[PDB]
Image 1 (tube, rainbow, N blue to C red):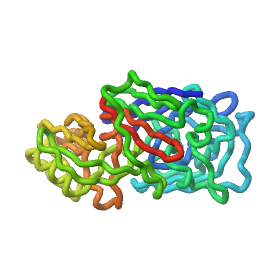
Image 2: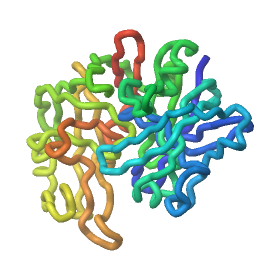
Image 3: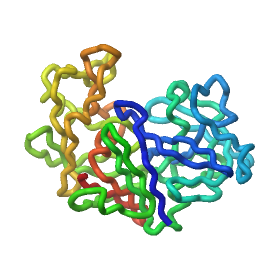
Image 4: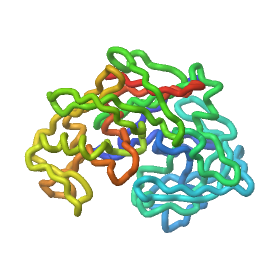
Length: 330
C-alpha cells in the first residue's frame, strides 16, 4: 500500500504545516501537524476542556462506530517549545492520503496548553519519530508509520515541504519526479528516539564550505533551524545590522536586509537554503526588526534541522530495519 497527502502552511510565514487526516467511521477529518520529532498522535476532542478549544475541529469518539476506549491508558506530553497536552486514549481507524491503519492509538486531549488553544489551524499532532518516545501509559503505543510500515510497498515516508506553498507527505514510495539529482542517504541514530543524523558542515552565502560534524535531528514539527552558536554567529555576521536580542529571544535583523543563503552538508552532497527562507518577518506587527530563521541551539541541548532546512530538500525517512535519512535537492 501507499498514501499521499498534501501538507499546507498554516500562515504566510510557514510557521507549521497541516495535513488532513481521516479518523473514525464515518470519517472525521482533522488537520494535523505531522511531527518527525515526536511520537504521539493526539487530537482536540469532545473531551477537551471547553475553554481550551478556540476554533479547532474536534474528534468525537462517541460518533465513530470503530472507536474503542483503550482502558486505563493516559498520555501527557511536553514539547521543546514549552507547550503541553494530556488526556486519554482511543483506538480507531486512521487514514492519511488513502493509507489506512486500523487500531491506531488516537490520543484524545482533555487538556492542552495555551499555545495550542491559540492556534485555531492545528487540530492535533501526528508523531513520526520512533515509537520509543510515545507517552501513552501504562502501555506505550505505536506511531501511525510504525503501524503502517509492514503493509507499505517500501518502509519509508517522505517529506516535501513547500516554501510559502503546499507540499506533500508520501508513505510507502519515493516519487522520483519530486526532486532533482540524486538522494544522498546518511546514517541515523535512534538512541534518543529521533531521526538523528550528522551533517558534514555548512557554508554561508557564497563562502567556503566548512567541513565539521553537526549532529542534529530532522524535525518537521519545529519551524526554525537551530544550530551551534558558532555556526549561527557566522551566518548572522554576514547580515548588516543583525544581532542577538535577549529580549526578543534570538537573532533579529533589519527587515530591509537581503539575507544570504545557508548550505548544509549531507555526506558529500549540499542542500542550499535560499536566504528568503530564513526571513520570519517583523518581530511584532509594523516593526522593521525581523526575526531570523537560523537560531542558536545552545539552550536546547540538541541541534534541530526544522522546517527552514527541510523545506529546501526532498527528505526520505527510511524506516528499514536499520533506519537512514535521505536528502535531495528539488
